[PDB]
Length: 126
Image (cartoon, rainbow, N blue to C red; front, side, top):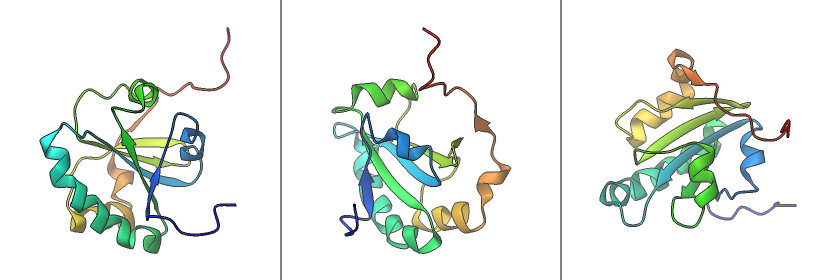
């Protein structure tokens, strides 16, 4: 299952999300109609390069084909990167540059970042 390696960047869907609740996962909400995104497009690709190398998965979400995910996180500003470590989500606070990224991972700088506690998807009480 998913043995082969297809594109360093994984494509998370309204169902794959679950996976994000396992191990480390780097997500980045981008948009095709958004200019800034076009600039990150490359910055992200270059990152995913050493991603798996530093023991960190990298995925990408589409705010045009995935209307659900967009809400599951309530993304208003873009682009926007989210660090998911064993369920613990942490908003990215950097220039979003290949270099920076590395540290954020290797230097686990994420530790010095306040996570988010607004995820209750799954066990619904109704």
